[PDB]
Length: 250
Ligand SMILES: *C1=NO[C@@]2(*)=C1(*)(*)C(*)(*)(*)=[C@](*)(N(=O)=O)[C]=[C]2
Image (cartoon, rainbow, N blue to C red; front, side, top):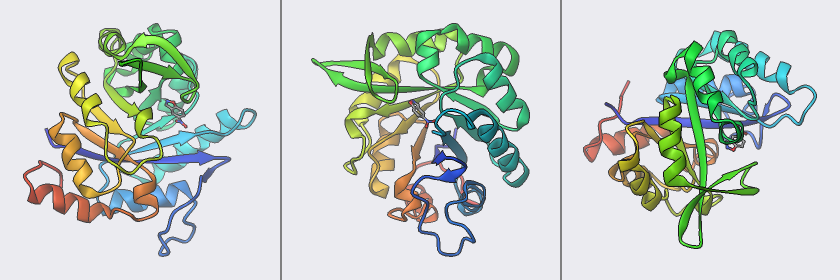
């Protein structure tokens, strides 16, 4: 299948954290209008990540999903502290196509299966944050704060076994960098799973997307490179097509 380009939007109290540089937008920090604009210029799927610190979070995420579903016609994922089946269920029913889970899945891997039982494997995305520690790829939880001691190799196999649809592979070793995706990490994971692998962290220029796809990624996700317009989405897709990558053009 076609390689996929995803945009992730980090949100807090209903706003896109640090906004965007699209002057054409009425409100460049509105996640709905920004998401809609991305869907029009060639983003394939959207990810909405909420960090509303406690209290209003549940209602905020549900209202976000409802507003997004009304306006956009490409698939989207919602994530950020989804801890149980009922939370995931209400977000999917309100409009999300998929839910994206990390810490709660590591702590209770049956959560993957429970969501998939009702909504299908295709509705369950597991985000795996990994980092090199003493020469092994280790799985990290709590926004990179906790080394679980679980090997990346073991967790990838378990995630597929439990019934996840896709894996987002986030390299903590590339957080905040613009040097490229962690292609070594992608190549390490590729033979271990039949699931779609979505690369995250490290993108800085168009050539990094090509590199990630050569490494075996099925999709590439980014955020600030798009929001601050370091990479244009249409230019990226034209570049990838030029060099033989199967991507969807309009
Ligand atoms: C995934 N792994 O750690 C995370 C993940 C997502 C979000 N988020 O804001 O959706 C936060 C931490």
